[PDB]
Amino acid sequence: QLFADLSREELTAVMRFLTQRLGPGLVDAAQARPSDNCVFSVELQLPPKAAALAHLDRGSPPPAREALAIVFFGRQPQPNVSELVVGPLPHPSYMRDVTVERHGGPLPYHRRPVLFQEYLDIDQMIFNRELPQASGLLHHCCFYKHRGRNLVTMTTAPRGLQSGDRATWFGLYYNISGAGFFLHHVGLELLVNHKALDPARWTIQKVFYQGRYYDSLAQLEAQFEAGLVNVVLIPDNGTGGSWSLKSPVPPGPAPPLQFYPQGPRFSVQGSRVASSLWTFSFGLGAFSGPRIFDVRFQGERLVYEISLQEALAIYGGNSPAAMTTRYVDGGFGMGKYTTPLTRGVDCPYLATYVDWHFLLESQAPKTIRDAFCVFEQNQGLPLRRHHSDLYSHYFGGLAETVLVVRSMSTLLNYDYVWDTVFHPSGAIEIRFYATGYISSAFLFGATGKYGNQVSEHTLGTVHTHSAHFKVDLDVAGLENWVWAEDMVFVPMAVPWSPEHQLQRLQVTRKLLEMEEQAAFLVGSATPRYLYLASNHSNKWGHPRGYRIQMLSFAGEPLPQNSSMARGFSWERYQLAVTQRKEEEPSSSSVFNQNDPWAPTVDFSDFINNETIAGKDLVAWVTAGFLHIPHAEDIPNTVTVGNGVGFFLRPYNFFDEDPSFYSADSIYFRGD
Amino acid sequence: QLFADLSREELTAVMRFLTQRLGPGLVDAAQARPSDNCVFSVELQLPPKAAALAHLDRGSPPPAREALAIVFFGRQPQPNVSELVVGPLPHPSYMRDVTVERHGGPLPYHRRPVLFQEYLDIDQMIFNRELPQASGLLHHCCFYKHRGRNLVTMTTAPRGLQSGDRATWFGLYYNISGAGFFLHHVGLELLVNHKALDPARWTIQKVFYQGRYYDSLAQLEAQFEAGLVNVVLIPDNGTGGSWSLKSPVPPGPAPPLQFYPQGPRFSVQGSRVASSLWTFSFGLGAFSGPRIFDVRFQGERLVYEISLQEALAIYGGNSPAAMTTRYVDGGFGMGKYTTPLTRGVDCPYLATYVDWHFLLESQAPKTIRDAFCVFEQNQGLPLRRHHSDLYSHYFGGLAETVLVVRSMSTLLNYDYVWDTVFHPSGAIEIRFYATGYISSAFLFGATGKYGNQVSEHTLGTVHTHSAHFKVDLDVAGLENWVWAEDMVFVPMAVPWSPEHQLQRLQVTRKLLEMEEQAAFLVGSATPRYLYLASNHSNKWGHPRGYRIQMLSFAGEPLPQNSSMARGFSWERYQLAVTQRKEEEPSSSSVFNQNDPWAPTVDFSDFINNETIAGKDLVAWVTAGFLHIPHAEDIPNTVTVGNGVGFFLRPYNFFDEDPSFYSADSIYFRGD
Ligand SMILES: *[C@H]1O[C@H](CO[C@H]2O[C@@H](C)[C@@H](O)[C@@H](O)[C@@H]2O)[C@@H](O[C@@H]2O[C@H](CO)[C@@H](O[C@@H]3O[C@H](CO)[C@@H](O)[C@H](O[C@H]4O[C@H](CO)[C@@H](O)[C@H](O)[C@@H]4O)[C@@H]3O)[C@H](O)[C@H]2NC(C)=O)[C@H](O)[C@H]1NC(C)=O
Ligand SMILES: *[C@@H]1O[C@H](CO)[C@@H](O[C@@H]2O[C@H](CO)[C@@H](O[C@@H]3O[C@H](CO)[C@@H](O)[C@H](O)[C@@H]3O)[C@H](O)[C@H]2NC(C)=O)[C@H](O)[C@H]1NC(C)=O
Ligand SMILES: *[C@@H]1O[C@H](CO)[C@@H](O[C@@H]2O[C@H](CO)[C@@H](O)[C@H](O)[C@H]2NC(C)=O)[C@H](O)[C@H]1NC(C)=O
Ligand SMILES: *[C@@H]1O[C@H](CO[C@H]2O[C@@H](C)[C@@H](O)[C@@H](O)[C@@H]2O)[C@@H](O)[C@H](O)[C@H]1NC(C)=O
Ligand SMILES: *[C@@H]1O[C@H](CO)[C@@H](O)[C@H](O)[C@H]1NC(C)=O
Ligand SMILES: *[C@@H]1O[C@H](CO)[C@@H](O)[C@H](O)[C@H]1NC(C)=O
Ligand SMILES: *[C@@H]1O[C@H](CO)[C@@H](O)[C@H](O)[C@H]1NC(C)=O
Ligand SMILES: *[C@@H]1O[C@H](CO)[C@@H](O)[C@H](O)[C@H]1NC(C)=O
Ligand SMILES: *[C@@H]1O[C@H](CO)[C@@H](O)[C@H](O)[C@H]1NC(C)=O
Ligand SMILES: [Ca+2]
Ligand SMILES: [Ca+2]
Ligand SMILES: [Ca+2]
Ligand SMILES: [Ca+2]
Ligand SMILES: [Cl-]
Ligand SMILES: [Cl-]
Ligand SMILES: [Cu+2]
Ligand SMILES: [Cu+2]
Ligand SMILES: [Cu+2]
Ligand SMILES: [Cu+2]
Ligand SMILES: [Cu+2]
Ligand SMILES: [Cu+2]
Ligand SMILES: [Cu+2]
Ligand SMILES: [Cu+2]
Ligand SMILES: [Cu+2]
Ligand SMILES: [Cu+2]
Ligand SMILES: [Cu+2]
Ligand SMILES: [Cu+2]
Ligand SMILES: [Cu+2]
Ligand SMILES: [Cu+2]
Ligand SMILES: [Cu+2]
């Protein structure tokens, strides 16, 4: 496996190599401060596609196993963060900054994501130096006690208002046991200015309490005991979903159970899963998230790569937090926040479960058990089917059984469900669901344009979800073209009665040659049939292609007049196809999160006058939808209807529905 | 069971009663001749909602169990086809001609569907009068031995060009045995003007053979014998999916499958199903198709009824038949063409199968085994789910299990799979797929405007699929309103830093008061969050409602300039909402198919400027798509991602996610 995420051991060797080259002033990033030199991350560095392919096809010698490590360099006059490529594994030797090379110049230190350590200091400063200045108020409303931390904080992004900032707003919640605190915002949000390399110089720029702005906790505290701050008492406990996840009702009859009568018909051999029809390797980007490479259907490779690129979530709000939150989850990392899968709930009780080794903000490799799960799910629905009683009685059909590869990313409040379905029809399905806990704020004022009240004093904040996927199809090879077929009604006379009129239905086919005419903004209509296809024809003389069908209800992307709108330019499209370049492996950056104003990676820069006619193309799909919270989002948001994504379906790629050749396919005559 | 379909006894009772009060001139519609009198169909006349609800949930006396019977009166000077509502079953007493009452006016005979007899009468005219006149041509091109009729014809629709017609176009295909004959067009189509009441009077107005139009079979045979008809010999046999339906590859490791560990959590008695969560009555309209009534989630009725209302398939092509086919399949009968379900393919093995009785084109009611299938399906995906590793390490999930009611209709070539899935969240999903075989034509000329080549000498005719559903919700009462909520970005300077700009995300909440406001034309933007609500609010003061999330890519509906458009005016809408009037019980009629030029039930008329505020409403959803046949549709077209419909989701209808109380919910802490 050329695409097997770095191994438990491999990570160890890269780290041992680094401790040695980066000098000893290097500290474990698990407890480093702005001024320390620490290794933020180390994971698989993807091999170039050319060499990658040569190895898989000619048999040529595979490229070198490299790893990308991000190191924060605070131990220096002009601190920076840099991308260094290490290798070749398993026994490293070289190492080389690529930062400037990849991003034109030095990566500004303020863009670096917030370290685990860095968060504590913020609570440190909050629960210790700050919150006390308003204990009076707190002793009242929120049961603050002379003991501490019966409350917790929650970050938001981006940090600030213009490029170069690191000012984060933190809501305060009740530290609820065994259930989401997200639903119990105490009403207080603080704008922490944590830009200084010295935690001693961090400050509170502004405070927002139950409706109004205060310059400091003190001033607020002051006004509270002064008698001018009316407080709405927030209960610290209760019953129902708003309070617990444990269902009050005792079990009944066991829910239908899925099982393989003769055992699993697939085989996860490391990162590569192999079944009767499909074969592929899988993984998880520490930041990008789930990814699959070299997808071969019955031997033939359709896709070189289908990877998650980014996740956005723009909030509308009542308070300052909600109001400015525009999370760019990859800034946190979908791989990193991948929660272990619960056998029986997250995946069928008899699914295969795989582990995930990572080296992020730490110096020794850790593992997430059951990060992924691969299994076969009998849909209950038939793939194909036809009952004939006319002229010749017979029946032929096939009940559909699919192959799923799942993984879940729990970024703070909600959990993402990354589903990759492999159909017997040679069709590939990609879906993602947003479930778990929604982000709520304190309810005050007319609940009109920011959400609905889902529970007392708690407001479901409106927001949009949007994910981006890289779909590096290599339909029947590397050089593919984009075709756009649709329909139309041509009025014309009836050949056998020119006295009458008919609306002749015809197909409308167009070739997309320029990246632009193949980039479709969110909102505008798209061709009913859109697909990338080969230069070569399938038996009946048609270019063998694979169609791209989407399932998006995507909200409107932040207006362009927004200076951060560039931090996630991909959201403005439903789809775009470009010349898959080696210098365009990602559509977003982990750095884009903390500084969307000055994108480390701007996706719109992938679309320029270029021919997407006979080149190595890559499609970019954006799926998403508007989420106006409501009662039934308590406790968790369900997955029903909320699962968006897209399809990769063959169109004249095969000379016939291969499922014809299904072992499991059924046939008989009459009854 | 006041919604339950009529059974043998009842149908018999009505028939017995009909042949009695109808008198002497009443032949068995099975053989009945054009100028005969016969009972075309005896079905259940749906009860007036008012009294239905009056009794159902109060105690009032149940309404008169009725049955609507349709008779073709041909044996008379002024032939009409009439709708008669028969007396109180089980022992019928009265009879009323509702034709004028109901449709207002008399039903022109030429609107009557073509009886299974007329079809025979036709084949006789073809084979035993016309086909021999081209014995020479056929004996060559088509292995045509006048012996055994190795060819079969296939009706199209509508019949005629202007209203008042009955001139069908029949293509001729090989009588393949045990497979689809649709993939084998012999290039010969015919225009049988079976308008007259006397079968001898019928004639072929035009003939079409492998490209050219001719005036008579004789004229063709003549030119063939003359030498001016270069025939392309269509192979009558061969292998692959185009000939077989039975997979060649033997059975391999068995596919996974479910099973209820402690038996099924749902019971089926008659037409009513009930589980811990759901309660409802199902059934099947003869032409209307699948329908469901009195849906109660834990006792609360959400919908009075949700039924299919019509199906349509508008075609394009180079061949006359194809070139003008606009199937309003309800003119055929989705109930009527419901084929038997194959246990383990069409539905899981461990499902509950149901029969269906009917008195159609016969004098004796017959039954269809396993017409319906009800079961429970562990989806193998989670409903709600959160894994906590931040602050408090708890986990709460619930893999989703759904309840399904299915039925499959086989209208000649394709089989429609009708779904309706009730989810543990109180969301009702309606999906329908199109599978089975396509409709092919003879290949020739510049191919590209009408379809792709899917096999030797056969084209995959471009077409559109659409289906209309009557969703008559009753959100906690009959008075429901229509809300259209949706986003918008409002720029305003950053409260705490005016120098900086901000894009304030907000929600728009507009109320639809007129039917015109609520009717949404296909291809036009619709409010993201659109739903019907009650007057009454939930514990958090928001209106109690259900939103209608749509799932369709409806291809452009037939223009309006076209003479027939009105026959299926609903196809021009994605959604529309109206006042549940008892006289607007259906969006289409069985009689519309043969007279699209003079619709028996014009749907555009259901949309007049009436207030849809605080009334009993009903939504009309339209879901469909464009189908451009491709190789992978051979042997059959697969369901994968071709299932369109919609969801009925609870929106502030509950005080929370009702699944929090799932007995099957899961919770715990740590691993
Ligand atoms: C689809 O196309 C590929 C590649 O064809 C490419 O052709 C070039 C010119 C670009 O337009 C690119 O966009 C196309 O994809 C097919 O495989 C190759 O097909 C090309 C023809 O298009 C073959 O190239 C020719 O090769 C001969 C000698 O082998 C050359 O002499 C030709 O060029 C001469 O003339 C021009 C103009 O005077 C000069 O500029 C040149 O210097 C030469 O003097 C020409 O390039 C090529 O041989 C094919 N591949 C091989 C080596 O087997 C592919 O088969 C096709 N698929 C189908 C079925 O449609
Ligand atoms: C981000 O900061 C790192 C700091 O590690 C920068 O890399 C450093 O680059 C300097 C300049 O080449 C290296 O300095 C050394 O200076 C001595 C003094 O004579 C010379 O003899 C050595 O040959 C060497 O050049 C330093 O070793 C190197 N450190 C590492 C581990 O990379 C880096 O340039 C900054 N990134 C960007 C994008 O500017
Ligand atoms: C269709 O024909 C029927 C024939 O039964 C007409 O109704 C009957 O008409 C006869 C005399 O023609 C009366 O004696 C019966 O009492 C009528 N009852 C029935 C059976 O309907 C009917 O008027 C005609 N309707 C249309 C469509 O014009
Ligand atoms: C909700 O409406 C009920 C019936 O609607 C009519 O009755 C009055 C509200 C009147 O204003 C008409 O215009 C309405 O269309 C009504 O009887 C209930 O009292 C109403 N309940 C609530 C919660 O307002
Ligand atoms: C939150 O409280 C729980 C117990 O209620 C404790 O285990 C956890 O460490 C606390 N964390 C914070 C942020 O106070
Ligand atoms: C919340 O209330 C319940 C019942 O009223 C009580 O049992 C529980 O201890 C409370 N929550 C906690 C753990 O403090
Ligand atoms: C695209 O590039 C061409 C040059 O090849 C130029 O003529 C044209 O104006 C450009 N169109 C755009 C995207 O403005
Ligand atoms: C087709 O062949 C079957 C085989 O038994 C025969 O019963 C049927 O009559 C034939 N249909 C035709 C050509 O009408
Ligand atoms: C087609 O040929 C096969 C021999 O391979 C034969 O079994 C079959 O009967 C022929 N077609 C039919 C069913 O008439
Ligand atoms: Ca480009
Ligand atoms: Ca490619
Ligand atoms: Ca109306
Ligand atoms: Ca209603
Ligand atoms: Cl037309
Ligand atoms: Cl903004
Ligand atoms: Cu290898
Ligand atoms: Cu900086
Ligand atoms: Cu309160
Ligand atoms: Cu491992
Ligand atoms: Cu049958
Ligand atoms: Cu980078
Ligand atoms: Cu959400
Ligand atoms: Cu929702
Ligand atoms: Cu009753
Ligand atoms: Cu007439
Ligand atoms: Cu029965
Ligand atoms: Cu855990
Ligand atoms: Cu009618
Ligand atoms: Cu179709
Ligand atoms: Cu298709």
Image (spheres, coloured by chain):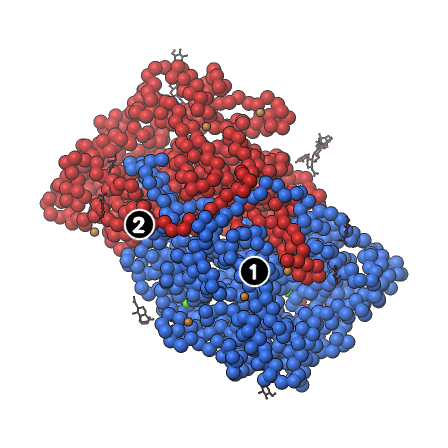
Chain colours: A red, B blue
Residue most toward the left? A226
Residue A15 position, x and y percent, is: 41, 20
Q: Please identify the quarter of the rendering in which residue B359 is found.
A: bottom right
Residue type, label 1: Asp
- Look at the image and tell me in which quarter the C terminus of chain A lies: bottom right
The residue at 65%/51% (across/down) is: A667
- Look at the image and tell me in which quarter the N terminus of chain A lies: top right
Residue to which mark 2 is pinned: A248
Label 2 resides on the chain identified as: A
The residue at 51%/77% (across/down) is: B90
The residue at 22%/31% (across/down) is: A124
Asked if one can make out residue B355 in the rendered structure from this viewpoint, the answer is yes
Q: Secondary structure at mark 1?
A: strand
Residue to which mark 1 is pinned: B370
**Is disc 2 in the same subunit as disc 1?**
no
How far apart marks 2 and 1 lie (CA) works out to 38 Å
Report the front residue among A269 and A478.
A269
